[PDB]
Image (cartoon, rainbow over all chains, first blue to last red; front, side, top):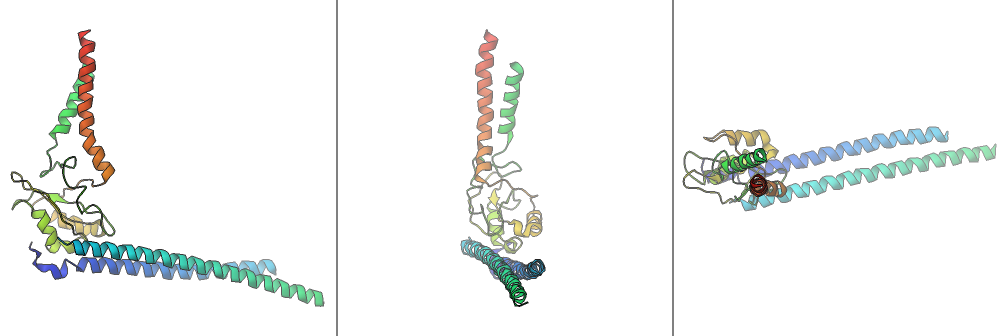
Length: 52
Length: 56
Length: 147
């Protein structure tokens, strides 16, 4: 159509992509932190069992 | 053309990728530090048990 | 030898049958598609062209239209042809479903080509390779058959 709808085409797609990327990065960081905590607990349990 | 929009989107994606890599590295460093702390705690527990054995 | 020459000639004819853009056959060998600003996107690669039923340079303008949200792509392009309307549109795989929807919601069916530099160069040189195969088949088989 016409380029007169710049308000939803010039930057709306960019904002949506940036929001999706930021959400994915935040979710990945949170999941990595949770997995790191779980693995740390497991390693602590294993090391404590070996030392015991 | 929307060269400004293209450049903004590309820079935003690059910054997001860099932030994701930094967050992954920070999580890995936290896991490594927690593993080191767990090993130190296990060694301290073993040392306390050895001190208890020496006291015995 | 005659069969090889005929096969090389058929290959050259098939290579030349590809219309240079503005139609279902692209001009990636000698067009501005791989070198356009659509080459790489933020998280995808932009590739789109059409044979518009309205006017030439329509796919360049259509990206500037509301379709720019139908795929996170935006880029300048120099694609035109008077006889058959030629242009290039912008569409990114980050909205691959929506990008395909934007490519299909028009008078032209989806039409895109490989913008990778190595693939573009290989495709461009494939025609030269077919022509060289025909020329070498001629040079060899003609002398061999004269003998």
